[PDB]
C-alpha cells in the first residue's frame, strides 16, 4: 500500500533574520500525500549558480536554518519529500536570500523644484540595488523647518523617486533628508536644504 510521497512541499521560502543566516521554510505535506506513517524533507541549497555540489540535509521539521552565510546573497533551494519507500518528484527550485543588512546606498539629488510658497517637489535618483543590502522597501523623506525641533517625514514606496511636500511655512529655510530602507532598516541620509518663497 505504501509508496513514495505523492508530492513535494509547497511555499518553499528562504529568508534570513541575521546577515549570517537564511531560514528555509515550507508548508508541511498534508498527511494524505505521505503515503507512509512518517515523512521527511530532503533540503538542498547552494549559493546561486555555483558548480560546487548542493549542500544537503534531511529533516523532519518543516524548516532548516542555514548558518554562516554572506550578507544578503541569493541561494537556490530545492525541497523534496522522502519516505521509506522512496522520494517525491524531482523538485522545483526557489530563490531565497540570507538576511538583510542596513543599506549602504545614499540617494542622490535630482532636484528640488519650488512650487509655491507652501510646497516643493523633491526628486532623487533610484539607488543602486546592489548597495541596498536587502530588498528595497521604499524611501523616507525627512524634513523640518530651521526658521528664516519638530521633524516631519513622508514614506514612499520603492518604485517612487519624487514626492511633493505641502503645508510648508512661507519664506522659511528647510532641511531635508532622504534615505532608502529595506526590511532591516534605513541607510545613511543625504542632506539637503531649500527655502520657500514669500507668502
Ligand atoms: C522614517 O524616519 C523616521 C524618523 O524620521 C523613522 O522613525 C523611527 O522608527 C523606528 C521604528 O523602526 C522607531 O523605533 C523610532 O523611534 C523612530 N524614530 C523617530 C525619530 O521617529 C522611521 O523608521 C523611518 N521609516 C522607515 C519606513 O524607515
Ligand atoms: C531566526 O530564526 C531562527 C529560525 O526560526 C530562530 O531559531 C532564531 O531564534 C531567530 N533569530 C532571531 C534573532 O529572531
Ligand atoms: C563560513 O563560511 C566560509 C565560507 O568560505 C566557510 O569556509 C567556513 O566553513 C565558515 N566559517 C566559520 C568560522 O563558520
Ligand atoms: C501649492 O502647490 C501644491 C502642490 O502642487 C498644491 O497642491 C497647492 O494647491 C498649491 N497652493 C497654492 C496656494 O496654489
Ligand atoms: C508602484 O507604482 C504604482 C504607482 O505608484 C503603484 O500602483 C504600485 O502599487 C507601486 N508599487 C507598490 C509596491 O506600491
Image (cartoon, grey):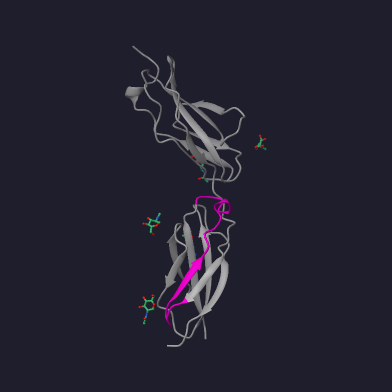
**For residue 100, above or below residue 87:** below
Question: Considering only vertical position in the picture, is 162 above or below 4?
Answer: below
Q: Is residue 194 above or below residue 20?
A: below
Position of residue 138 measured from the top left corner of the image (x, y, whole percent): 47, 58
Residue nearer the viewer, 89 or 26: 89
- Name the foreground residue: 172 vs 29: 172
Residue pictured at 54% horizontal, 45% vertical: 99
Q: Residue furthest toward the left?
A: 32
- State whether residue 71 is above or below residue 197: above
View quadrant of ligand 3: top right
Quadrant where the N terminus sits is top left
Image coordinates for residue 177, horizontal then vertical, percent: 53, 69
Residue at 48 percent across and 82 percent down: it is 196
- Residue toward you, 134 or 117: 117
Residue 118, magenta (yes or no): yes
Residue 199 in the image, given as x and y percentages of width and height: 42, 88
Percent x, y for residue 3?
A: 38, 15
* Left or right: where 128 falls relative to 87: right
Part of the protein shown in magenta: 114-135
Identify the residue at horizontal 46%, vertical 29% (top origin): 79
Question: Which of 1 and 172 lies nearest the eye of the viewer?
Answer: 172
Q: How many marks?
A: 0
Choose top left, top right, bottom left or bottom right for residue 154.
bottom left
Q: Residue furthest bottom?
A: 199
Based on the picture, tell me whether residue 85 belongs to the magenta stretch.
no
Amino acid at each position: 500500500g505504501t509508496a513514495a510521497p505523492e508530492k513535494n512541499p509547497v511555499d518553499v521560502k528562504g529568508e534570513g533574520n541575521e546577515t549570517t543566516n537564511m531560514v528555509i521554510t515550507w508548508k508541511p505535506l498534508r498527511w494524505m500525500d505521505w503515503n507512509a506513517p512518517q515523512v521527511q524533507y530532503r533540503v538542498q541549497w547552494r549559493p546561486q549558480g555555483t558548480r560546487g555540489p548542493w549542500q544537503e540535509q534531511i529533516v523532519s521539521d518543516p524548516f532548516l536554518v542555514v548558518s554562516n552565510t554572506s550578507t544578503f546573497v541569493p541561494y537556490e533551494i530545492k525541497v523534496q519529500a522522502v519516505n521509506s519507500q522512496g522520494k517525491g518528484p524531482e523538485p522545483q527550485v526557489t530563490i531565497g536570500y540570507s538576511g538583510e543588512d542596513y543599506p549602504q546606498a545614499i540617494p542622490e539629488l535630482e532636484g528640488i523644484e519650488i512650487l509655491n510658497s507652501s510646497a516643493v517637489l523633491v526628486k532623487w535618483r533610484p539607488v543602486d540595488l546592489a548597495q541596498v543590502k536587502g530588498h528595497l522597501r521604499g524611501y523616507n523623506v525627512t524634513y523640518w523647518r530651521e526658521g528664516s525641533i519638530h521633524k516631519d517625514h513622508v514614506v514612499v514606496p520603492a518604485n517612487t523617486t519624487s514626492v511633493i511636500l505641502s503645508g510648508l511655512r512661507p519664506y522659511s529655510s528647510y532641511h531635508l533628508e532622504v534615505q532608502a530602507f529595506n526590511g532591516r532598516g534605513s541607510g545613511p541620509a543625504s542632506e539637503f536644504t531649500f527655502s520657500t518663497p514669500e507668502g
